[PDB]
Amino acid sequence: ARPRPREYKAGDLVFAKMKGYPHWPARIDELPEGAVKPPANKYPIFFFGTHETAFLGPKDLFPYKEYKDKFGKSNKRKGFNEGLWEIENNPGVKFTGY
Amino acid sequence: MARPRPREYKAGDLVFAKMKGYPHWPARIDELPEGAVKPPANKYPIFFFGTHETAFLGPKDLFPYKEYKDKFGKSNKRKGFNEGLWEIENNPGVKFTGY
DNA sequence: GCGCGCGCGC
DNA sequence: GCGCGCGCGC
């Protein structure tokens, strides 16, 4: 079983998992120099569709393409179908990384 | 040393019956009246409280009710379980044709 | 397997 | 605003 990665980098597209929500189309944001240091090994997440943000570790992240069809099915939670759209057609919304 | 569960049961006896996939479950030995197709060897007709389902099971899957009450008697959220706990105390002869 | 809850319908 | 379907988590 090919492992899910243990480290990600700014700009990667993923599905992210939070309790109560289905695996959600998302992106690894940049971690700027200059800020308060995040929790260890937790990554800055940008959810597509909602543009909400959080920090998550690799345990809850899934590479977009690889895990696409297990997770990319339409669903009625507000903003989900909008996220499916953005991750394909405008994946860089508010992307500061580069 | 450990007390044997009964290897024989009598019509009317109250038990927890175990079935594959279900928790140990509040139940009763029904009568097997003559005039019917004979049961399989050493199996008893079982009445499940709450669901009122029925089946045949052998001594190995039956546990005397009072004795095993505290090990199996706590609430469970399978459909009709708690309704069974209730019945086995308050209306245990429901649909009992045995006597 | 089963109850909660979100999100849409009527 | 209340019902119901379906997907969440336990």
Image (cartoon, coloured by chain):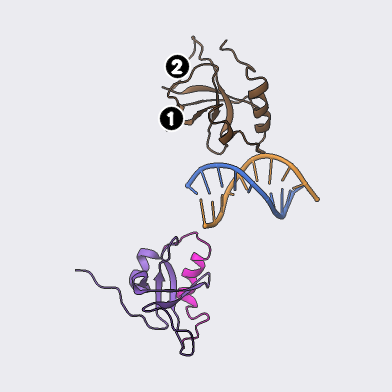
Chain colours: A brown, B purple, C orange, D blue
- Circle 1 packing at 10 Å, graded few (<14), some (14-19), many (20+), is few
| Mark carried by residue A2 | 1
Q: Is residue B95 above or below residue B73?
A: below
Residue numbers of the magenta segment: B74-99
The answer for which chain carries disc 1 is: A
Identify the residue at horizontal 51%, vertical 11% (top origin): A32
Q: CA distance from mark 1 to mark 2?
A: 31 Å
Identify the residue at horizontal 43%, vertical 67% (top origin): B25
Q: Is residue B9 above or below residue A64?
A: below
Queried whether the magenta region covers residue B92, the answer comes back as: yes
Queried whether the magenta region covers residue A61, the answer comes back as: no
Question: Mark 2 belongs to which amino acid?
Answer: Lys
Q: Residue furthest bottom?
A: B35
Left or right of B7: which side holds A33? right
Identify the residue at horizontal 41%, vertical 70% (top origin): B17
Between B63 and A90, the residue placed more toward the observer is A90
| Mark carried by residue A37 | 2
Q: In the rendered image, which quarter contains the N terminus of chain B? A: bottom left
For the stretch drawn in magenta, what is the main secondary structure?
Answer: loop
